[PDB]
Image (cartoon, rainbow over all chains, first blue to last red; front, top):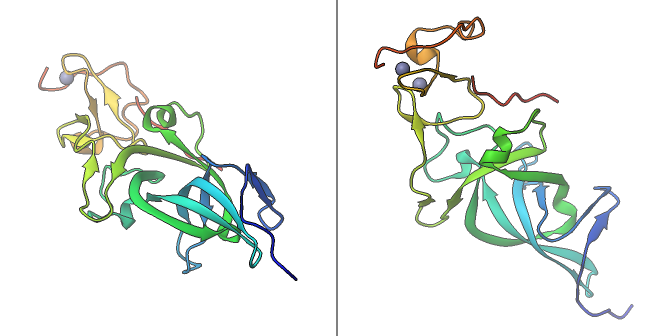
Length: 185
Length: 8
Ligand SMILES: [Zn+2]
Ligand SMILES: [Zn+2]
């Protein structure tokens, strides 16, 4: 035929996806390695190219810890991602499904975490490898940042929180917790 | 105690 103009869309819905997305939404996008886990992205813009025609999506990349320069670390959550310097444009049909990037705080407040739920406490730099903020709060004797996956427990003099394994204690110890005092007290 | 449990 002949081609229609390019148009920026309020929203786009895909039959394969079966879900309808708008700008500002977070999505999972198939990487070229299909076995590889989905890329997490934030949709800045949706646009249709009349030539194809096809739909292009301007995405800002959310990096996984294992995609970061530093690599994954102990205090890094399973569903943790960093908002990154990296922008790209992808096909609309590379989208598997919608997802939610919560604030670290709101993620902590979540009753149950599904494969859809993620959290972000770090902004990220793709070239340098810088983090913003450069540091957060730390806890226990390991003096490491908090991983919401893991279980900690509070006390009195310290009123700090501890990994049981870090102090001989059981995973099972704190259930039967009349209460907690730690040596530093 | 602090934890967010993941189930689905
Ligand atoms: Zn203490
Ligand atoms: Zn610890």
